[PDB]
Image (cartoon, rainbow, N blue to C red):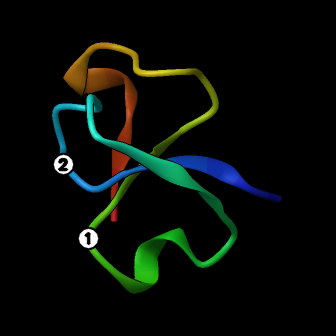
Amino acid sequence: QEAFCYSDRFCQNYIGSIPDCCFGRGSYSFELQPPPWECYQC
């Protein structure tokens, strides 16, 4: 329910994991700090 949230769309700014990831700046992925294209930008 908690995808990894990266405030930046390049997936390298991990702020944690939250299920309300898209209620702020965030790109979410199910992997730890992957390449920019592997995250979904909110």
Instruction: Determine the residue located farthest toward the front in the rendered image.
Output: 15
Q: Position of residue 2 (x, y in %)?
A: 74, 56
Question: Horizontal and vertical percent for residue 21?
Answer: 51, 69
Kind of residue sitting beneath label 1: Arg
Find disc 1 in the rendering and name its residue. 25
Residue that numbered label 2 is attached to? 8
Q: Residue at x 26, y 29 (%)?
A: 12
Query: If the image is split into quadrants, where does the N terminus sit?
Result: bottom right
Secondary structure beneath label 2: loop
Locate residue 26 relative to residue 17 in the image: left or right.
left
Q: Residue at x 21, y 25 (%)?
A: 36
- The residue that appears at 28% across and 14% down in the rendered structure is 35
Q: Secondary structure at mark 1?
A: loop
Q: Residues within 10 Å of mark 2 (few under 14, many from 20)?
A: some
Indicate the position of residue 27 as horizontal and vertical percent values.
Answer: 35, 51
Please report contact status of discs 1 and 2: CB closer than 8 Å, yes or no: yes
User: Of label 1 and label 2, which has the lower sequence position?
Assistant: 2
